[PDB]
Amino acid sequence: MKRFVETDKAPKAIGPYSQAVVVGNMMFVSGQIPIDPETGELVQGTIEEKTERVLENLKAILEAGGFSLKDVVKVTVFTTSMDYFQRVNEVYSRYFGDHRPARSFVAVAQLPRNVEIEIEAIAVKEG
Amino acid sequence: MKRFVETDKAPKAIGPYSQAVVVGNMMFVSGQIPIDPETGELVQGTIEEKTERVLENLKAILEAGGFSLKDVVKVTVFTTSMDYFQRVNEVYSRYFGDHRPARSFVAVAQLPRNVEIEIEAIAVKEG
Amino acid sequence: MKRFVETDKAPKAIGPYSQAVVVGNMMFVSGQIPIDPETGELVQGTIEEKTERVLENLKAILEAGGFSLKDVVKVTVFTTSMDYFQRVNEVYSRYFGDHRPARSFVAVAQLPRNVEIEIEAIAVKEG
Image (cartoon, rainbow over all chains, first blue to last red; front, top):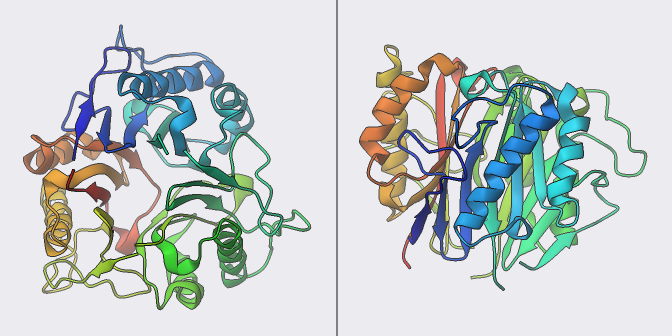
């Protein structure tokens, strides 16, 4: 294997896991929740604001390991309700509208800290 | 990175995502739901008929990018109920009975368009 | 592609899937549930005991294909309740506290055999 990503620009991986793991030209990013990296608190407001935070956390992790949003190949969005699909996609498009990685969008029963949105991703670069 | 897959033989990726993304010898396919690629409507009938459509969509995407079902290494089945396990496996075996990729089968709270079955996959070819 | 993993030290993959699939230097492990590989029965007791069984099954599969826990890059934990987070992490740390792979921890509606914990993983080795 090769290296782990630790950045203060995304929430600290408190437990037995890392924000991301880089092996060769591939990065595996941990599921990001709407937590502010500096205050450690949950963003409380609209689903667009929560999705913005999640994608900002994801972006910071990619960039901390030498990756970018253009390197992302597969994304998985977890939510507590499909009612958020349209609005989540609206914010999502502002990050991946040009790039367009593969994706699955599913609604689970419950997320960490009782959040409503969580997004993980796999990225690959070079060629 | 390398290339994206767009085919009329699987449902059109409407939003900010692609049906699949091919990077090197790897393909990351988006979660497929029981939608007919030509009419755009949800298959309404038995769970075998819905699983058939999902796997046909998956197969079309693989084949549109130069991949096949034999290249599939990991699959993830999402459902709304585990009651469908036996019957989903029955149809699934007709596509991957010989090949036998790694798999996770989980039941979530809700899926896009309120469907009951969704299947994503990762494929790798060559050697 | 390259090879499949079959070991009596993890529960037998009964249906149309394999315990894991090794392609090149990568392994894709199937979601493991708290089943005893020898008796085929569900571990019934505390969530720590169930997590131990799941991680023991995962470990056996990795080791049967020439991989180890240090090779694991991405893990996905599925549960029926987030109430188990702290205790699952406690047992999880005893397997991946040093290594620290990327991770997502989500709570779904239902799991196979009505279990409360299921863990899948991707591993990569060499360099």
